Amino acid sequence: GIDPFTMVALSLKISIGNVVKTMQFEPSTMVYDACRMIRERIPEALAGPPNDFGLFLSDDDPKKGIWLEAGKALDYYMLRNGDTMEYRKKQRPLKIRMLDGTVKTIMVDDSKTVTDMLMTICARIGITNHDEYSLVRELMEEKKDELNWLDHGRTLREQGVEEHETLLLRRKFFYSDQ
C-alpha cells in the first residue's frame, strides 16, 4: 500500500548480464522480498523462472563475491546507496561427464554446496543414489593444477572455481550395482 519510503531505501545498481537497472530497496528488504519486487517492475529480471534467479553481490574478487540468501537482509552486509547488486541466475552452466563418459551441461545453483549440486546433477540422469559419488573438477588451473576432487563440503567460489571447465562425476562408494 502506501509504505513508508523515507531516506532509508538503498540505491542499488542491478546488473542483469548486460543491462543495468537502478532499484531502491529498504535497509532490510531481505533477498526474498527483493526478488519479488525486482521481478515485478523489471521485466528483464525474469529471463526464465523466478525461482532460478537470485541476488549475487558482485564485488570484484571471486572470493569476496557472495550470494545473497533469503535468510539475511541487504543492509546486513555492506550494502548501501551505491552498491552494484547482480540479479542473475542462481545456477551456472556446469559441464559434467557421467560414468559412461557422457557429458551434459546442467544449471546448478552456485549459492549452495557440492552435495546438493551432485543431487541436482545425478537427478538429471535419473540416479537416485547420488551420495555414492564424488565430484572432480578438471580445470586449467595455473596455480593448483588439479583434478580438484570436491569434498562435498566447500563452496565453489571459495575454491576459486570458474564456470567453463569440465567436471567429472565419479563413483565414490562401492555400491557395485549391488
Image (cartoon, grey):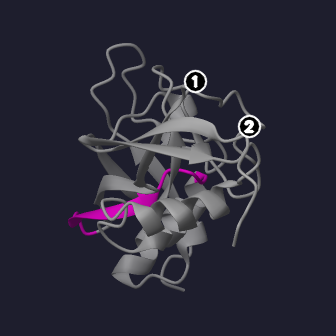
Q: Is residue 96 above or below residue 84?
A: below
Q: Is residue 44 above or below residue 1?
A: above
Q: Identify the amino acid type marked 2.
A: Asp
Q: Where is residue 39 in the image (x, y as percent from the top left)?
A: 45, 65
- Please provide the residue range marked out in magenta: 100-113
Residue visible at 56% across and 53% down in the picture: 114
Horizontal relation, residue 135 to residue 44: left or right: right
Q: Distance between the residues labelled 2 and 1?
A: 16 Å
Horizontal relation, residue 73 to residue 15: left or right: right
Residue 171 seen in render? no
User: Nearest the camera: 56 or 94?
Assistant: 56
Q: Position of residue 157 (x, y in %)?
A: 52, 35
Horizontal relation, residue 156 to residue 29: left or right: left
Lower position in the chain sequence, tag 2 or tag 1: 1
Q: Identify the amino acid type marked 1.
A: Lys
* Residue 25 inside the magenta-drawn segment: no
The residue that label 2 is drawn on is: 75
How many other residues sit within 10 Å of disc 2, few (<14), some (14-19) or many (≥20)?
A: some
| Secondary element at tag 2 | loop
The residue that label 1 is drawn on is: 64
| Secondary element at tag 1 | loop
Q: Is residue 177 above or below residue 67?
A: below
Residue visible at 32% across and 71% down in the picture: 48
Residue visible at 36% across and 21% down in the picture: 145
Q: Where is residue 6 in the image (x, y as percent from the top left)?
A: 73, 43
* Residue 110 inside the magenta-drawn segment: yes
